[PDB]
Image (tube, rainbow, N blue to C red; front, side, top):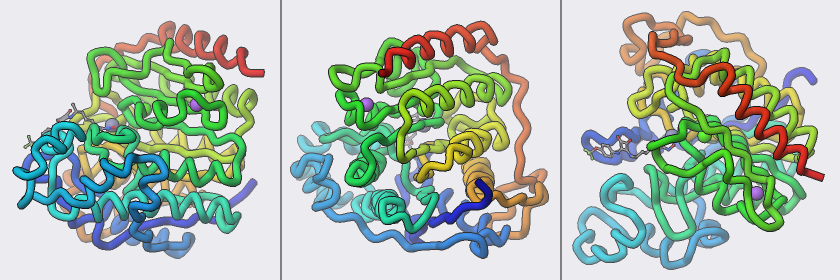
Length: 369
Ligand SMILES: C[C@H](CCCCC(=O)NO)Nc1c(Nc2ccc(OC(F)(F)F)cc2)c(=O)c1=O
Ligand SMILES: [Ca+2]
Ligand code: NA
Ligand SMILES: [Zn+2]
């Protein structure tokens, strides 16, 4: 029990990577998070590391050599010469070409793999990489603003020392990239809670339960618009508890995508920072080596609030609602508070729907030996 050792990864350059004018993915939110938690004084309670830049040698442990060579070569000045390669790898539109794309992928991946190495070495209880959690990237493809799947790479590192690794994804979108990589193995159980029905990426049906050796090791909780803290918490704690009891993993990876928060530019959920962070508190109570990662989140003031509070939660540190002064203070107007209020949006997930989906998952969890 009690307070635990926390290692946090951050590179001072991460906030300078720009996806382009009008693009919702803003790496600057990672800097906003870092600045906000330094101003709360949370650096006193944790070890801050600079990630290494993950190499091609590291990336090719999962990704194809051809895809990684392309990512390492593509620049906005040579796009015309790589036209075929761009369409094949899904680069240029949703996943645009930008200055320092590869470096950005290296730093994002570096923090996740370094966190996994630290946990494997038993030198920390928790590792945090807010620049990670890029769950959509595939063996040979970019998708949903994700080029390199840092989660898969970090999980592969944990598998060197851990027989069973549990993956939890509280981003509003299905973590299809992670699920795909470990679909046919029982050495990784993937658990995703996401909006489902005519929504990106279009995967993550209740009936998608894994295949072969991995059958019953892929868990999906499909949800509708406007889920609140009360509905989410009532299903999250029982599902994770049953997963912990049945699967008994030795390490956990928690993807904390903040696009499941109320008011998100691309999200349809109605969670508050408190409701989102209760997921961290739940997972932390199991006392297993834990890797906390980023993901989506497009109302960057709420991403900074979310991930600052989730770091404070990892540290068992009570932080006041009144925000301290920081370099992005004006972003947190008009209230300048850490916590957010839900909107008036209708919760399309009834309590009966929530209970029925939970019961269906419980039947699948009983199939585990
Ligand atoms: C459907 C796909 C969903 C990606 C979710 C990834 C995630 O959170 N993973 O958990 N992509 C989308 C947009 N893309 C978009 C791209 C560029 C852009 O700006 C532009 F380039 F157009 F100027 C505006 C929107 C949207 O806007 C939007 O939605
Ligand atoms: Ca999810
Ligand atoms: Na699996
Ligand atoms: Zn997302």
